Amino acid sequence: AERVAAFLKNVWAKEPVLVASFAIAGLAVILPTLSPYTKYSLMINXXXXXXXXXXXXXXXXXXXXXXXXXXXXXXXXXXX
Amino acid sequence: XXXXXXXXXXXXXXXXXXXXXXXXXXGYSMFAVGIGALLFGYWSMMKWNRERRRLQIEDFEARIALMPL
Image (cartoon, rainbow over the protein chains, first blue to last red):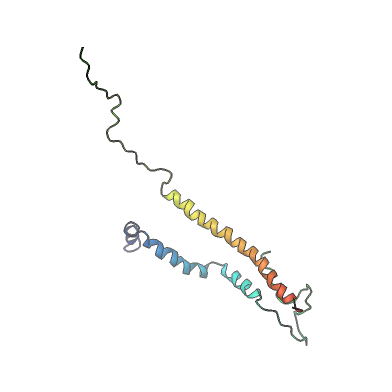
């Protein structure tokens, strides 16, 4: 190698802290795209309500029931 | 009899001896504990934030439940 192997040990010797400035900040962009865990965090952010939920008038509707615990809508129960 | 200052050397105090030596840290072994504490750090912290989510949804549920308010 002309740039991979040559410009690595010299960077560790001369100005060694500059290695960390490119490696840590670089991997900070790569990791949130390839690793399959980021999709879970987006769901809980949207599920947690900030304001009170609005009630709609019932006229031929599916997956919608009363306020009591029943199998209706989505309702998040991901990981305990 | 003549009495003067007597000569004594015994151990010679050791002429120029190095005391500075590598201790505790080796090099590669410190990174295994260093970055190892970081990986243990995030895993312990994020589990608490998932336990915070149990409290979070339950806190906002109180506002939805209270309509006479």
